[PDB]
Image: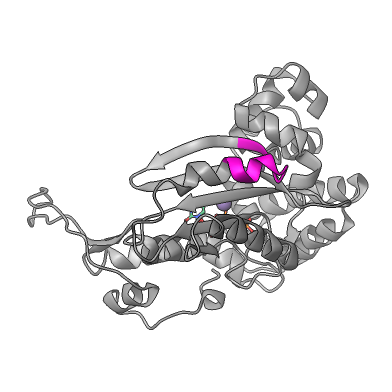
Amino acid sequence: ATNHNLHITEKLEVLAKAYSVQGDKWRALGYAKAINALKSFHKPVTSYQEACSIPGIGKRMAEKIIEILESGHLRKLDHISESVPVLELFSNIWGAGTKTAQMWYQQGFRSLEDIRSQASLTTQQAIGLKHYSDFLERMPREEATEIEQTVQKAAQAFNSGLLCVACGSYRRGKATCGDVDVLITHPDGRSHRGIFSRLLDSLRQEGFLTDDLVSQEENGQQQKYLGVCRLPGPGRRHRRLDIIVVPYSEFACALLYFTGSAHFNRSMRALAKTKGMSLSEHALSTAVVRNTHGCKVGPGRVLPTPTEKDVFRLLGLPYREPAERDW
Ligand SMILES: Nc1ccn([C@H]2C[C@H](O)[C@@H](COP(=O)(O)OP(=O)(O)OP(=O)(O)O)O2)c(=O)n1
Ligand SMILES: [Mg+2]
Ligand SMILES: [Mn+2]
Ligand SMILES: [Mn+2]
């Protein structure tokens, strides 16, 4: 027959072969399964939404297809059979993008050895290399749950009524989580301040937190810690952990943003701008007032959002349970 998506299929085929011979035959199935669906398609796929609707392609496969599509250019060097398996090897290193991967490829790096030994490495990328095998795998939902309770009970020792919620893939009801994003705040809006610094070292001492990506990131009034953790006991693997501390005022919108999905967020922002608003991770606020000619005449004000439901209300949307916002 005739295959419209020739470009996507060739890369996915070389990609699938590499994974089966490298040990993962589960994912090579996903690529192979995806390839058959792609071949039997009337038109060339060039977008995310279109890739998701196709029978046989999941919403985590679509993101992978998009990555390949966006990073196609230049594809000038060598051939796909020798480049792509090496490109993916560097791509899966944490804190390394496709551009950083092909960059290392241009320099002449073919193994993870060459990356560690010679290549320039971010403070982030170094950590990924150390825990690369463990970072290649998603974690079961149950493992994410006891990580949630670990951070939760560790923080609640400081403040009894302190609230900790997992907003990653976990909250969306996903069966597997690449990482676990823990959001922490307090109902009064008073208690959350200062907890961040005195909790990290508390968790670091017990051997729970192994490495730190960013010691502390200050965005507005939000605190973010990117890092790595390992559960106690034998046979435990290292899981990347993201902690975000927000004021209770921004909690509803921070909850919604971090909850997901990524494409859901993008769709929410796109919808918010059509109703004359803007949806950040801080608060749902009215869009900047502009005259007819597009000149910025007025500042946008912040709307009060105490609950996650009120955000949906103000956007004229019927509420959607986290399981139903996995786009
Ligand atoms: N470019 C991005 C990345 C993330 N997020 C938001 C939505 C995500 O759900 C959330 C957490 O980021 P993750 O990288 O952890 O995404 P997921 O948890 O949903 O998937 P994964 O299982 O790989 O962690 O942050 C976003 O809005 N835009
Ligand atoms: Mg997550
Ligand atoms: Mn990566
Ligand atoms: Mn994350």
Residue 196, position in %: x, y? 48, 46
The answer to which of 209 and 319 lies nearer the viewer is 209
Up the image or down, 260 lies above or below 231; here it is below
Q: Residue at 74% of width from left, 19% of height from top?
A: 108
**Is residue 193 toward the left or the right of residue 242 in the image?**
left
**Is residue 49 toward the left or the right of residue 277 in the image?**
right
Q: Quadrant of residue 103?
A: top right
Q: Residue at 81% of width from left, 57% of height from top?
A: 27
Up the image or down, 90 lies above or below 29; here it is above
**Is residue 83 toward the left or the right of residue 221 in the image?**
right
Q: Is residue 309 magenta?
A: no
Residue 125, position in %: x, y? 65, 31
Q: Which residue sits furthest bottom?
A: 318
The answer to which of 237 and 112 lies nearer the viewer is 237
Q: Which residues are magenta?
A: 201-212
**Is residue 197 toward the left or the right of residue 175 in the image?**
left
Q: Residue at 58% of width from left, 61% of height from top?
A: 168
Residue 222, position in %: x, y? 39, 48
The answer to which of 322 and 61 lies nearer the viewer is 322
Residue 111, can we see it? Answer: no
Screen quadrant of the C terminus: bottom right
Up the image or down, 317 lies above or below 257; here it is below
